[PDB]
Amino acid sequence: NRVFVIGVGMTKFEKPGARDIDYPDMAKEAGQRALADAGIKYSAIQQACVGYVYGDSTCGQRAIYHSLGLSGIPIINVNNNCSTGSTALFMGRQLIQGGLADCVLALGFEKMENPMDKHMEVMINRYGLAAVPAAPQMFGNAGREHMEKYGTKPEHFAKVAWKNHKHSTNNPYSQFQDEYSLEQVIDSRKVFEFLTLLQCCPTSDGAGAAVLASESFVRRNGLEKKAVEIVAQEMVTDLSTTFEENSCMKMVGYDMTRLAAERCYDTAGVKPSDVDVIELHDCFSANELITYEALGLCPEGKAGELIDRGDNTYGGKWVINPSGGLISKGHPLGATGLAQCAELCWQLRAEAGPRQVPGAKLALQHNIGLGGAVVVTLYKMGFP
């Protein structure tokens, strides 16, 4: 069964406490924007898939009833107690593709609240980073491994972050919308090793939403115009390996990204060179830089050359994170994938305004599930 995104919506992503509304009003703003975009009656929604990390099991229902009114529809919380949760969009795609529903709402939101692990926990709190204590150490280790094997420079990681902040200047939904100089990225507060504060994603509070529909729902309702097809979607969980084969890059999911993308390319019958625009999970600059190679944009060890050619921005081969990435937008855990989806749908619909990638036809999304698995998605217009 083919699956289409027929409406998208999001709140602005803002510093926690910047905006004095609670998570149900954030959900309502994003959800009602997606339903207005879709152009459907609220009663068309048959099930809701709701992604959030903080708060008890009733928050998904509370947010949906505040957004749509009271109803009997299933309300599925993405983040189950197995800690193997995917994403609201991934689950909504499953329900359509599996013939369990014709039309679903995917909703996501977040409203915050050894000695090195203790130091990183305090740093995360005081710097407002959207990371767990292990993450800066694991991503710094992966970055350092890439430098030692391939000759990548610390400045290549800073240039990735610089490019994301530059893109953010045209995204009114992003927490940060200012261009920093490369020297300012390098000179910002140390987080871990070469990673500085402007290379790490901050916390944001916010919400995002998407309306997903079957081919028959799109046809019956005449909604071909805005229908963005999910032409491939793959999740890959931790790949059990040996001591001899393990590496710092594998420990942060390099091969999970690589296999998810390979499977998407095969399903969609496309190559990395066919992709026009990308939104990826730049939790740290180091994740974006190695993800260039995992996605097959360039050969092993060649990300520094891609960066130095400007082949990750406007006028280059790929426009990567036209949104400004997690580095600029910040990272409300449950909402990040739906914000990526909103931007890629606007790009393919030619509605991304000052961020528009001219002629974009194939979009790739890279994201991490609430349980840590990598999800890669490919999008094209359904009815061009």
Image (cartoon, helix red, strand yellow):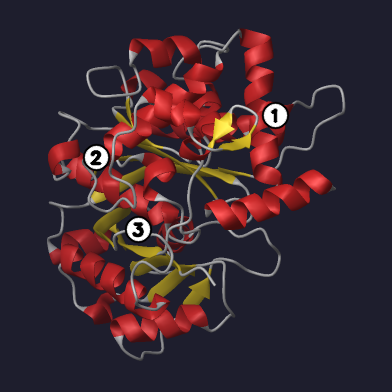
In which quarter of the view is residue 195 placed? Answer: top right
Give residue 268's position: percent from left, percent from top: 39, 33
Residue 332 visible in the displayed image: yes
Report which residue position mark 1 lands on: 141
Identified at 48% across, 78% down, the residue is: 60
Identified at 33% across, 16% down, the residue is: 310
Q: Is residue 81 left or right of residue 64?
A: right
Whether residues under marks 1 and 2 lie with C-beta atoms below 8 angstroms apart, the answer is no
Give residue 292's position: percent from left, percent from top: 48, 24
> Earlier along the polypeptide chain: callout 3 or callout 2?
3
Identified at 17% across, 52% down, the residue is: 226
Whether residues under marks 3 and 1 lie with C-beta atoms below 8 angstroms apart, the answer is no
Q: Residues within 10 Å of mark 2 (few under 14, many from 20)?
A: some
Q: SS at mark 2? A: loop
Up-down relation of residue 176 to residue 96 (above or below):
above
Report which residue position mark 3 lands on: 13
Q: Which amino acid does label 3 sit on?
A: Phe
| Cα–Cα span, label 3 and label 2 | 14 Å
Report which residue position mark 2 lands on: 169
Closer to the camera in the image, 149 or 230: 149
> Earlier along the polypeptide chain: callout 3 or callout 1?
3
Q: How many marks?
A: 3
Q: How crowded is mark 3: few (under 14 residues within 10 Å), some or many (20 or more)?
A: many
Q: Which amino acid does label 1 sit on?
A: Asn
Q: Is residue 39 left or right of residue 234?
A: left
For the C terminus, the quadrant is: top left
In which quarter of the view is residue 214 placed? Answer: bottom left
